[PDB]
């Protein structure tokens, strides 16, 4: 999740 | 650094995960939102970009029962709906 969220 | 002030419901959510202020940068708002999703374990186990928020405070704030982190514009749109951009 964090990995994806950082993309924002 | 887009300076913003969360409306009542969003501020409640941010505070529930540690936030102490009333004025934040968009980066800070995203950080806390992320921590909320993690703490509540709202993401899908297999495809962690999927978030389930039906019957949850986040669902009331965003107005959707689920969403994917891949939906960038939608997320920013759902977030800005709960914020005011400071004149500063």
Image (cartoon, grey):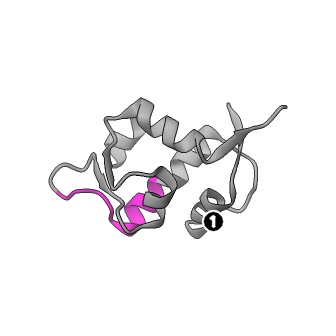
Spot the residue most to the front: B63
Question: Can you give x and y, in whole percent of width and height, for residue B67 in the image?
Answer: 32, 46
Crowdedness of circle 1 by 10 Å Cα count: few (<14), some, many (20+)?
few
Question: Can you give x and y, in whole percent of width and height, for residue B30 in the image?
Answer: 53, 45
Q: Relative to B25, does residue B45 appear above or below in the rendering?
A: below
- Split into 4 quadrants, where in the image is the C terminus of chain B? top right
Is residue B47 in view? yes
- Within the magenta stretch, is there residue B39? yes
Please state if B67 lies on the left or on the right of B9 as rendered: left
Is residue A8 in view? no
Which residue is identified by label 1? B12
Residue drawn at (48%, 65%) of the image: B57
Please state if B75 lies on the left or on the right of B22 as rendered: left
The quarter holding residue B15 reads: bottom right
What residue span does the magenta drawing correspond to? B34-45
Please state if B46 lies on the left or on the right of B39 as rendered: left
């Amino acid at each position: 999740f964090m990995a994806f969220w950082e993309a924002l | 650094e887009t300076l913003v002030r969360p409306k009542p419901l969003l501020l409640k959510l941010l505070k529930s995960v540690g936030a102490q202020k009333d004025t934040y940068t968009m980066k800070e708002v995203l950080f806390y939102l992320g921590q909320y999703i993690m703490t509540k374990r709202l993401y899908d186990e297999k495809q962690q970009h999927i978030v389930y928020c039906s019957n949850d405070l986040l669902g009331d704030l965003f107005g959707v029962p689920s969403f994917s982190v891949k939906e960038h514009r939608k997320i920013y749109t759902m977030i800005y709906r709960n914020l005011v951009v400071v004149n500063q």
